[PDB]
View 1: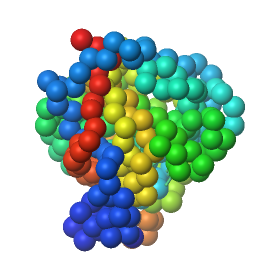
View 2: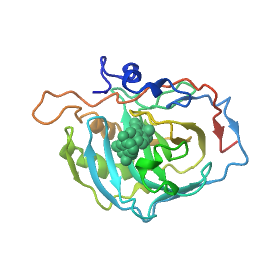
View 3: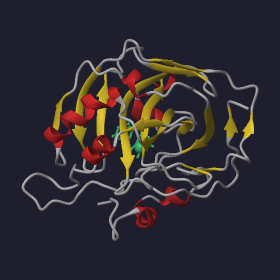
View 4: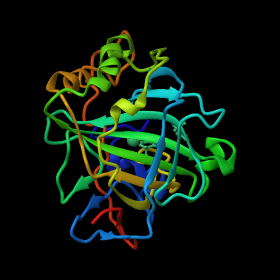
Length: 257
Ligand SMILES: O=C1Nc2c(Cl)cccc2S(=O)(=O)N1
Ligand SMILES: O=C1Nc2c(Cl)cccc2S(=O)(=O)N1
Ligand SMILES: [Zn+2]
């Protein structure tokens, strides 16, 4: 029932999901002058060499690439994290215009899109159990700006025609997510939530400072996806982002000076 339209969008979600007005909701605005460098943070460890991608799917709210998480193959460790977090999927949020689309903002600046690489804490055994824990998930968030093409994104964009409508999936094996990463792993981190229903407050957010550049042609392909299912009137999948939520009693920590 929930979505991104006028009658089912973010301002309505609290009725079905009262945690929408909770104490650690995401996304947030990252005020760069107020985020404090934390020298006790460790460098991120992003170990994606053994990643096994499986499928790509249009779920009616985004498109998502899934991974085999039945073994420690592609894992996120270090930084603010205790223990090992397994990559299980990535997806994006994007806009109808280049000046909007990201969920997190930086000094109120919105990027054209935001990539979420979703990982779960292996101490909880499965992702469903992890989402019930305050430290169950770690999401690596990466901003997209429009400029030069990102070569590592092209294989994604070229398959989107085959998953145009809600409910479509396709094989998407042998995709290397290392090609989506910027050079620097400098990051901000804070405790938050999923940015869609169920809005569970289970995420350690790790948002990279350096955006990746993608071309106008790449992002235009995102905007040709459909929220609707096959054999229905086209409603373009655009502006599938939740706006910044109140920071409340939280501090955003920077890994860098
Ligand atoms: O699309 C997804 N939805 C989820 C929900 Cl609703 C709850 C828990 C985990 C997931 S997920 O990250 O596996 N992929
Ligand atoms: O829209 C989002 N939904 C999520 C779900 Cl349902 C599960 C895991 C992580 C996410 S997310 O917060 O990265 N962005
Ligand atoms: Zn997301």
